[PDB]
Length: 493
Ligand SMILES: CO[C@H]1O[C@H](COS(=O)(=O)O)[C@@H](O[C@@H]2O[C@@H](C(=O)O)[C@@H](O[C@H]3O[C@H](COS(=O)(=O)O)[C@@H](O[C@@H]4O[C@H](C(=O)O)[C@@H](O[C@H]5O[C@H](COS(=O)(=O)O)[C@@H](O)[C@H](O)[C@H]5NS(=O)(=O)O)[C@H](O)[C@H]4O)[C@H](OS(=O)(=O)O)[C@H]3NS(=O)(=O)O)[C@H](O)[C@H]2OS(=O)(=O)O)[C@H](O)[C@H]1NS(=O)(=O)O
Ligand SMILES: O=c1ccn([C@@H]2O[C@H](COP(=O)(O)OP(=O)(O)O)[C@@H](O)[C@H]2O)c(=O)[nH]1
Ligand SMILES: CC(=O)N[C@H]1[C@@H](OC[C@@H](O)CO)O[C@H](CO)[C@@H](O)[C@@H]1O
Figure 1 (tube, protein in one colour):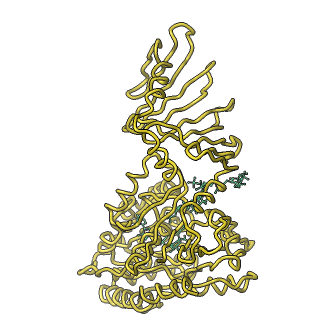
Figure 2 (cartoon, rainbow, N blue to C red):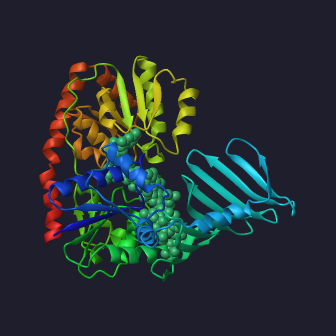
Figure 3 (cartoon, rainbow, N blue to C red):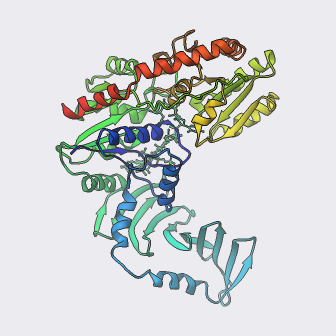
């Protein structure tokens, strides 16, 4: 009866909390006999390989389907032919016939016509990927992109060598979508779906049509929008019965802002709460802040579902401080390096294991070296097994300035690893009980945080006691039953 469609930009293998919560939410709805699938809107040439990898890793439940806008029309297109598009491949081969090949490296080569003496093509082969750039009067006109020698995309270039047009090709090499690209901002213009002879004014129009085709207009159909920038796709559909929910995963205020500004995407979701079935926030404090600040009522608090597995059989007695996150500015890993410097200057035995990848990773690497912490702080890369990494840590640290909730802190507490976190909006004070299951540090206070890490790393009994109470607190306050009943209460009203 009930079926759920959870919307986000894309799915990939080295992501953070938002997709992690969608994957766990899907598992919980399927266990309660409610199919809950993921709808994505990006274009990938190898989506089938991403899905298999996420499922093999155990991140994505085997029952979770991913519905993708390009995949839907590509699959319709695949059914149209039996034979591969031999003529497109013959056309490409003919344009390279009667040329001079000039090799630059392995995989890289250039082609010059024997008669016109001019530069025809550039080919770059790396692994399973191939790119063929064609030229006219020493200017790049087009690029054909291949995966396992099969064309998947053609891009056209303007005078400034910027993308002005794209064509997507199915599994047999036939075009199924063609679209204009505004080279000034990279936005998608008029899109033509060759397979059904339908044209759309832009990508949002295509995505709105797609959702109306995918999701039947029944009260049993439930749309949950997780990706904030994706909210207009769900919001603009013509559904009269299907339910619409927006989940806000972050602090709705603008990050690194003293003017009090609100994030644009989240502001649009909140302001439109009364026009949909509900806008979900992860903590009670955010719901109250929103209600005080905005003229809306449809704000509901529903925590992320929590996966309570078995606690690691042994406590880490070694001075290992862990940190598992997306390496992004809001996590303030620079403050963690500054804290590490203080902890290491009072105790040189304490190790800091930092997992993840992101924009700040290089800045942080240079920062450890400049502070000469290369013997104590280790950038361990992304982990597909955070639960196993958690066993190696004595405690976990959070210098993050903004959260919606904080699954890594919650995950550490489930593995009996106490958290030392800056008391920020939102999340830490909901689950950390200061001096009972961890420590809540006054925001920016790097000295008091360094002091609490030192007390904790050098006290085996306190570290074990805090961790034990931490798992107990999560089990008690984040039951799957109460969270599922909160969602069911909305779906049934
Ligand atoms: C006239 O042009 C002007 O308006 C149009 C829209 O109006 S129109 O309909 O009249 O044409 C604007 O075009 C639209 O918006 C563009 C844009 O916002 O850039 C663009 O949207 C697409 O691309 C965005 C960027 O993609 S990215 O892959 O390069 O980042 C994308 O938004 C991004 O979403 C990701 C995400 O959710 O994955 C965000 O990343 C964040 O979350 C990740 C996942 O979380 S997790 O925890 O790991 O699981 C994290 O990994 C990541 O660290 C984190 N980044 S962080 O900074 O928050 O820490 C990322 O920040 C976003 O940028 C869009 O996805 S969406 O869900 O937001 O919709 C995506 N839309 S899609 O292609 O349809 O999927 C498009 O060109 C267009 O989108 S639209 O929906 O088709 O309308 C146009 O820009 C504007 N030009 S302007 O006026 O000059 O500014
Ligand atoms: O190397 C890494 C880094 C992050 N994560 C996961 O990404 C999520 C991060 O969640 P959180 O809410 O703490 O922060 P967010 O990424 O949403 O900003 C957690 O479930 C982590 O286990 C992971 O699996 N491996
Ligand atoms: C930094 C931040 O606010 N992250 C939140 C969010 O992640 C997604 C964020 O990338 C979207 O831009 O979602 C997680 C799961 O709900 C929260 O636990 C987490 O706090």
